[PDB]
Image 1 (tube, rainbow, N blue to C red):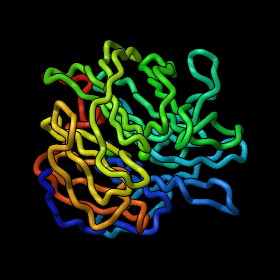
Image 2: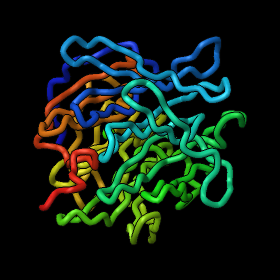
Image 3: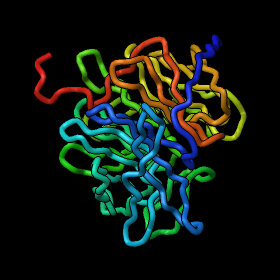
Image 4: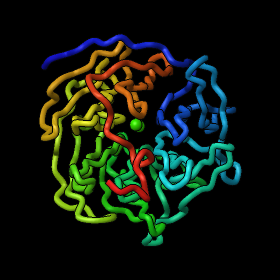
Length: 312
Ligand SMILES: [Ca+2]
Ligand SMILES: [Ca+2]
């Protein structure tokens, strides 16, 4: 498998569990520190990063009823400059740039207790596909599906429904949506970390997925596996292979990686493209830092970059 070794330029450091890199509608960059703890208890943070200086500013330290969150994944909304954050203790949060937030769901559409989330992906229709590797949200005792298969998948629809679309995953992690050229969502890809697998489904409609299938295989026998993911403008899927020192590159059809990207660290966690560029910002857990490197092409436009009132 061809392996490229681009130059990684340091962005910022010392972010415990450095995760969920994201750009908002203004081009501002955000990172979440899920593993920040105070006295041994969760006290995760959502930070804004000045790309010019690398200086960190924590805008939100989410907590509901004394229970601190473990914010791990992000997506920027389109109709409003706000962030949808997957939290391992609080579920789905909507965080404003001013630092204020709101917990989206205590229970799903079936009245079942919500599970802690890790990452999410907006389809062009506005539906948010979320991975829930943890057990029930706070105040429930913290649990995560690294060893047992109780991880779930949700779809938070445009009409405000938190619908559980599947379960029994061994730590569902990164997630991405494949769209047709005309913009129609048609395939959901989900990473199952420890199993070294990437799963896929046919998106039949909002919160409607069918035909679960092992779409791709993650290299290595190291502890870890597929973490964060995203598509480039050509629909190639870059996946951070946590613990492998590489970011895997899958073709439109999946299977085995058609290329790998060597990182100057062992634990790449998540990644995100800077709008209108080839620049990929990468978070990693070896040094708990953020880096950036140039990819061969631009990224696939995020839902937040699309237009509600566009013509084409
Ligand atoms: Ca993740
Ligand atoms: Ca991303």
